[PDB]
Image 1 (tube, rainbow over the protein chains, first blue to last red):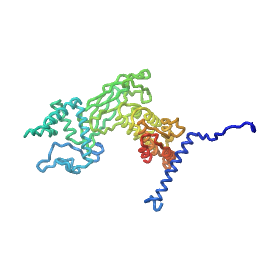
Image 2: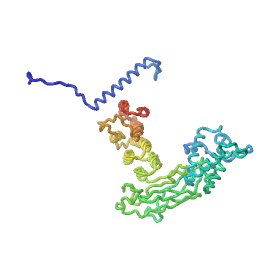
Image 3: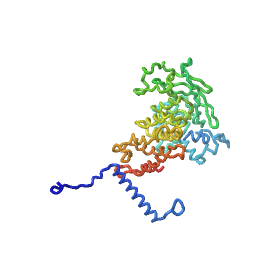
Image 4: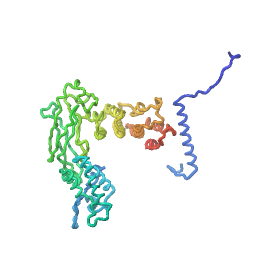
Length: 52
Length: 400
């Protein structure tokens, strides 16, 4: 079969349930902290310590 | 609110009485004037005024039929709406001032009972009554039979209320109710239960309807009693102090037909104990259809008692198993995440529980590290618009 016949490649299952929703929720946390850092250094800023 | 405020402060009194003629007659001048005036009082005072207003109308339920209350109020509003909406009957019009005296008169016209004692107790002696109804145990194979003493004295803010009655649950039997007296150095009996013996055979001789329960777990050699109560319908303004066997408290938490009883055994077992059976019965209470806020204070019971589990860490890191065994989204492989609403038992319960989990501390550095990281993970796994319910307060109490 290694020369004559052929096959088909789908190649991406990735269906690991808890791992999937870990990916999604971790990404949501990322976008949270990203926009936080952005408007953090963007707008009027007051701190918790001095100069953070 | 009422007990806390009138033990902070003096009474909240409902005068008919003046200090007319530049007279005071104000023991309740612990801060300020009240008699003729709105604008002396505190919002603490005015709030508790309304609260005593609720509960004294409950006492008027306690002496008089609700149907008669409908009768009274219909007569009130009949006379008022009659006296309204006319050509101003001259000199004959102020029937819409329907104040205390003639109202009382109309009550007694509907049913004249001894409610002027009710007045001079509660309307006209602004005092909260604690209760040292001291549990004794006769028919502990005792010659004397099912007896408990009545006791009270605690000044600063005290009051002595005598003739009332007492509500007791037997094993599987009668709601025993027993009179009270003044001159309160008293000893009293119970309308005795049967010889509840061979109770392996007497499994359920009709506890309360078709309720189903079996434990010989209590001190059941000679305990034909289950629960003490004075006035479960909460007649007298009360703060009741007594002691039972802890078995009886926990078994009341196995079931009772009063939220009153359930949260007060919640408080009584928040004080002292730590068996793991306490933890067990607590969790058992948390997992049924019983009540919402019962379970919230039950969470705080677990908080106190697992804080008493420092050297006695016998149970697990608590309540993680409760999020395990009560919460399956898609069987929840080790973490509960998504869309857990529309069942508002679970709404309040998920809203409450991780706070009491964040209380769980044992003295090394009080070390709730697993709980810490777990709660951070809870904050991770929040829902999209699949929840139609604005995932808001859940965030708020995870933050708290």
